[PDB]
Image (cartoon, rainbow over all chains, first blue to last red; front, side, top):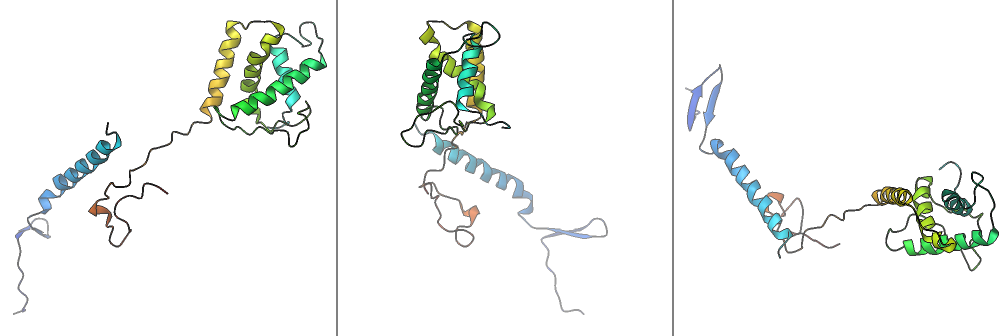
Length: 50
Length: 150
């Protein structure tokens, strides 16, 4: 046999192409939108203190 | 642009616009009024070096005297505004009062002058304000925290 042993998190075969997925691909958009929200709030707060 | 705008032309425009010395009403013109107008224009530009700001007027070099044949150095886009302001300042020599339409024209021309000078200074960041880890201050840039000075 070929001595390479693959390990997958979640694997499916959809359209002649094998597709995999880990545990963080689904959470990219909310995370990088939360970061933008915090960054935009910080400097707006820092612009006019009193 | 095109023809250079001399100092005497502005005062002649101001005198014409209120029917004091022009070929369209009765004519006539006096040299002392011209000298007074030119000196008024000089002093009014000197004052304008503060509130409206510099607009490129050319002052007399040494002691000398302004003279009406000297080049003003102003673009032709400003002559109406300058002339209306000068007329407003120098009307009271002849004991005359402006009419509402002249005031409206002067205000419109002055607003056009004001529009061509705005800056809107665009306030900065403070200086103790952090810059995030997304900016990668280790290697790409240096000096985490904004400079906020320069």
